[PDB]
Image 1: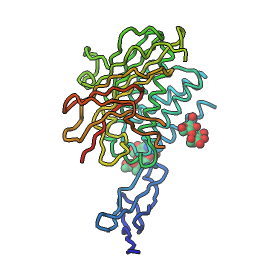
Image 2: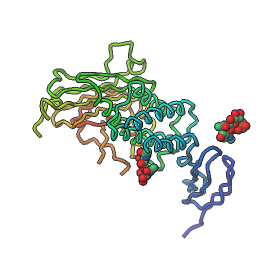
Image 3: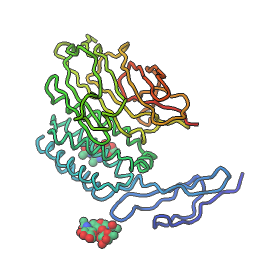
Length: 351
Ligand SMILES: *[C@@H]1O[C@H](CO)[C@@H](O[C@@H]2O[C@H](CO)[C@@H](O)[C@H](O)[C@H]2NC(C)=O)[C@H](O[C@H]2O[C@@H](C)[C@@H](O)[C@@H](O)[C@@H]2O)[C@H]1NC(C)=O
Ligand SMILES: *[C@@H]1O[C@H](CO)[C@@H](O[C@@H]2O[C@H](CO)[C@@H](O)[C@H](O)[C@H]2NC(C)=O)[C@H](O)[C@H]1NC(C)=O
């Protein structure tokens, strides 16, 4: 039983936003050369006064991205399908290189990479080495620091960056399947370093360290990093619950700035480290085999850092401290001891 506050008619971004009650959305179309819609929320301030939030472009798609996604079906309608996907990948890379995404283009880009990854899988087609590099460069471009606000916009409607991590893991597994036994490839870009290894069960005799630190062939930012994971050898033992014919694909990923966009799903909580991933297929027994993850802090003045892993069991899942012990090495570094495979990070309260 109170006054009903209304956001005034407004013209931000050359569109008419009609008078709209607090709590409600206004809708509009997208700029020229895009399709979809825009929306804008009217909200109530701490002091009970209506104000407009920023317009969302989460559902605007640039024409070139839409045309790209539609051309994918044309290539499907095995070799044709796979060569097709390689062309789509090349075209996506060129696009992401022009930047000037809409938020909706970030989402569309993930959807394209997802459809490309699923197509490779269904067609039993392994992309060539330059296609692998192109895929990673695309991801690195999507994760440009500049896109941070657009990702936040996109993520009002869909967990695009989580979906992107999943697409990255699936792609890694497709590539690993086509590798030789014992083969190890590093993918390096400005924002992402990935390691992919094919490892026969029982053949791993020492713990595996990622990323390798001793080489100047390694991109600067990662070589510099004090982030790393030690993967225990025992997890590569065959279990009757796997045998001498079993082969694991091990992927490990270090992200330079994925921390800027992954959701924390908690109030006054921030991601306070880079993001590190360890993925193994088929799944081994991991119980009582602890990965040791070392993560430098991003910022000082945080309350109580703690190790989490991504739990896939909506929002495509959540962060959990279940299965991780947090070791507070010093004010600037934390060591996580986790007996589950996943995406790892340090959260902390900012208050
Ligand atoms: C919207 O997209 C269209 C293409 O569908 C753009 O038209 C391009 O205009 C340039 C002008 O040099 C022309 O060389 C290109 O051939 C043409 N693109 C295509 C694919 O044919 C259009 O760009 C427009 O930008 C405005 C600011 C102005 O320079 C105008 O001349 C130009 O057409 C895009 N429109 C907007 C608003 O960016
Ligand atoms: C492209 O990816 C999307 C989502 O991963 C696939 O789904 C399309 O969109 C909705 C949402 O899932 C589905 O209900 C539709 O059936 C899909 N549309 C089409 C064109 O079938 C979509 O299947 C993928 N497309 C390709 C070429 O693999």
